[PDB]
Length: 244
Length: 192
Image (cartoon, rainbow over the protein chains, first blue to last red):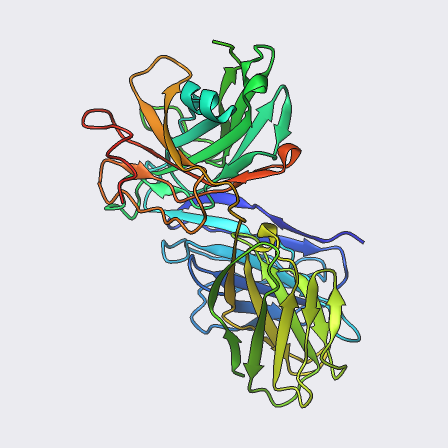
């Protein structure tokens, strides 16, 4: 049973570091693959294995390495980190008999190579109460949340109402935004909207909280700047229903 | 060896039954698969065909394999915005053991909502916590509307994003924008 398990799903790393993405399959599939798809492009197989002790490349210019010491593990690796590697990473495995089945559910590993790491910044969450106008006229309140000044593009926003993460009446920007596009290392920004019935918004017992999961550094990484160490964490902003 | 997919990009509305095709150049075949990779997520096995006909269903999905096997078509019925994703057609040189799969660049599928009883409008929102900054929101506009991008270094504008209020069976698009005070007003913003 069980599917596949890639880890980490998120991680920021400074050039020159030894990265070792890992993924395993509780399905016994002998065949495993490793795809990479830069942003705005399709899948490109880089490494594949038919089983233990078998390692094969798809794109001669890979720069990464793999090891199939076990049937369950096919961990990929990139000795020295480089900003050219910055992209997504998909681990794959396929059935062994009959009409080949394939499931590289591998949620993927979001990788971020940073030219030195003093360029890591957490987000600044902020919620905005609905325009009374919208309400009077529409009779529906729409809350907005804004993630600002955060690098790298590794976040997961969520809205919690009275203690429950909701999905209905919610829409986030599929793609974040660059505050200084002029910079290839420009800090990002992301918005999100939540809509409900005015009546619901007007009730002061109703609690609203826009949660944001940020994936920064690990407690071990070396930090020296005169500011808090941008470690993987969470930032939130909340609001309360008000009649007015 | 050569996997050809078309269209390459597409945009449609709900309730509509779309279809797309695949063509290629491989010596032998055995498996033909269609996936539904989502933004930042990994692909999904929707179907796998063999020398077995040009018809296999799975819910609102319908695959179709060419007789001589030179092209296939994935027929989708009553489109749902949740289906909006890129789909890849992948073939393989037969061999559950020694067969390689060639993916197609795919086709970015896009699904907008049915715009019935529209009502475009821009609202200025105030900060929950006392501050001097704010944001303008444009909402309830037909999907056909296009959201121009600030292009103004100091202004930030998000692309339209739809949300669905199941409880009320309502779906409304909406784009936001904001700046760092000064020469800013919901009027000039979102201006063509």
